[PDB]
Image: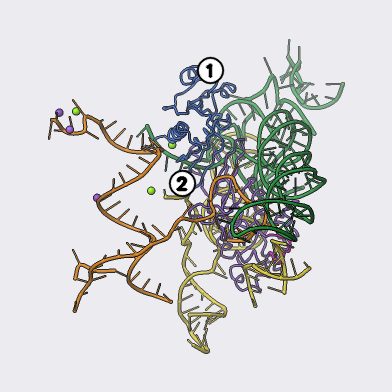
Chain colours: A blue, B purple, C green, D yellow, E orange
Amino acid sequence: TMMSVLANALRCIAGAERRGKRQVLIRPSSKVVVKFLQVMQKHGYIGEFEIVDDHRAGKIVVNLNGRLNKCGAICPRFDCTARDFEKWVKNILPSRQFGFVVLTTSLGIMDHEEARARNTGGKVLGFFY
Amino acid sequence: QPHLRKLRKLKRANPSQEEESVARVLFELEGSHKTLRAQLPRFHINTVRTSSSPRHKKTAMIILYPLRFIMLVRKIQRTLTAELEKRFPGNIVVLVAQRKITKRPNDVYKLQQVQRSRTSVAVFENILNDLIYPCDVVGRRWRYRTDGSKLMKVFLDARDRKRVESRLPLLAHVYKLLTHRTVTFGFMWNPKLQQVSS
RNA sequence: UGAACUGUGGGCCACGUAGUGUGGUGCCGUACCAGUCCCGUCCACCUCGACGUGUUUUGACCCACGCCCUCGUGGCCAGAUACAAGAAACACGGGAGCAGUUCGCAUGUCAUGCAUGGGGGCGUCCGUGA
RNA sequence: CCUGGGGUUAUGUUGGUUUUAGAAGUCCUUGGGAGAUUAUGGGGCCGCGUUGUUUCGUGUGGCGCGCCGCGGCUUCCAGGAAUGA
RNA sequence: AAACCAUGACACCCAUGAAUUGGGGAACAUCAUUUUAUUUAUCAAUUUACGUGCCUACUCA
Ligand SMILES: [K+]
Ligand SMILES: [K+]
Ligand SMILES: [Mg+2]
Ligand SMILES: [Mg+2]
Ligand SMILES: [Mg+2]
Ligand code: NA
């Protein structure tokens, strides 16, 4: 059965961008999925997306602009101390010049660059570049 | 005077002009109308509010009443609003029930005990149903633009277009005034297949 | 190892942005529609009373910077609405180095009596939690 | 939330008898304002008869609402507030 | 056991043309009797079309 909604959604987006599609449909939706997409959109990696209501878990349609190379989830959600950001950047990112690691902290869901500014650790959710 | 029985007990000592005018119309409607003669002697309102904007030249009149009479009002609506509009030219009359909202607690144990009718999401969507009552929502979408802006759109059945389209710009203003949230409206011919009118 | 949900607000200026719709203002040249005349019957042209395109402001999205909000509705203009067991409601001089902070005369004199003269925070116990 | 009823101190000190009041519970009653779900739900005692707003181009055209029945009494009754599938 | 697909179970995405096995919808048969729109268009407001053979001198509409 399906055990992770976030992992399912990120696999659908990465698969569609590999095939050069313009839109992708994601089902089911969740609060964590929407927050993850808002971080990607703020940095300019996807574009506009829309949520459709069906009185159950919703559906999401995402528009892709072709700037996203790969996104993925990290399972299980390992803890990350504020001094451990460099270790994760070295392991799962193409370089130290671009790309983001997404964390869930007591201040909310954010990328690793913002978390370093606020000096907070948390649990690693995923990445995109 | 007997017409003051249509107001809540606290407002009876020193009523406002708008509340007094509405109370007078309701009492006259009590003994005159045929259908409204029943189910009216059990009804009394809380307060009356008035809103307007430089655009939407018509004036909005909002009437709030206790939540107990929601079953009474539902059967009576589509007729009470028609007669009240006749006696108040230049105004559009809206009937909304007064509801309470429980602030979201922080403990998981406290959250499990919250009554779901007092949730903010549930209350706001019920106020929307109190507006445009004879029609019903056939769809709802949320749009997230490239900038942080977020929009909510509500679709209505296109069969009721001739009877509700004139009041849509004013009803969105009232919804913003009561909930501090913005809503956009659309019409859907064939809601089963999600076909948007144009 | 295990699906979704209770929820992240709004105003007022300012001014460099700042996307969109709705209306203002003038509008060379081009294009479109409607007229007039004219050729053709299988394939072409003229001249006008408007719509466009392009300006320039309004206005709603956006970021930066200040202020404000009982910071949904309602209810006041000290109580209630919510929140506070770091809370409320009782009480203890053996409780605060003299019973905390705020709107020379008296007692005693056989005395070293050489003594003594609204509301909010302190300490210590007892009832109140779902 | 309120007002009118009922049925441990302090008297100079210690030790004994006796009370007046509180408070509590416990039944009636007045004042007031609330309610997240309509006192109008059941019988019988029965008897009678079976032109005013609102769109849309002054005006036209659309506008929506309106233009076993009645009857007094009585007793019993909480039975609608629950995220969605 | 060459107990073989020499390929563990559950869940997601995934391009194309001919076929096939079971069920259903449309069709056949049986009954019953939106505005618009003179000056339009950026991802359409309706591609839903179509007949045959057998059949009471009944495991049958
Ligand atoms: K074997
Ligand atoms: K089969
Ligand atoms: Mg979960
Ligand atoms: Mg099920
Ligand atoms: Mg083997
Ligand atoms: Na084999």
For mark 1, name the chain: A
Q: Where is residue D36 in the image (x, y as percent from the top left)?
A: 55, 54
C15, above or below D68, in the image: above
Q: Mark 2 points at which residue?
A: A56
Most foreground residue, A26 or A17: A17
Residue located beneath label 1 in the image: A96
Where does ligand 5 appear, by image quarter?
top left
Q: Mark 2 lies on which chain?
A: A
Is residue A73 depicted above or below E30 in this figure?
above
Q: Which amino acid does label 2 sit on?
A: Arg
Nearer to us in this view, B165 or B129: B165
**For residue B87: magenta?**
yes
Residue A43 makes an appearance in the image: yes
Q: What element carries label 1?
A: loop
| Residue that appears at 56% across and 35% down | A47
Q: Is residue B119 visible?
A: no
**Residue A61: x, y in percent?**
50, 40
Residue A8, magenta (yes or no) = no
Horizontal and vertical percent position of residue B96: 62, 56
Look at the image and give the residue range highlighted in magenta: B85-92
Q: Picture quarter containing residue E45?
A: bottom right
**Marks 1 and 2 in Cβ contact (< 8 Å):** no
Q: What residue type is labelled 1?
A: Arg
Q: Which of B152 and E25 is in front in this view?
A: E25
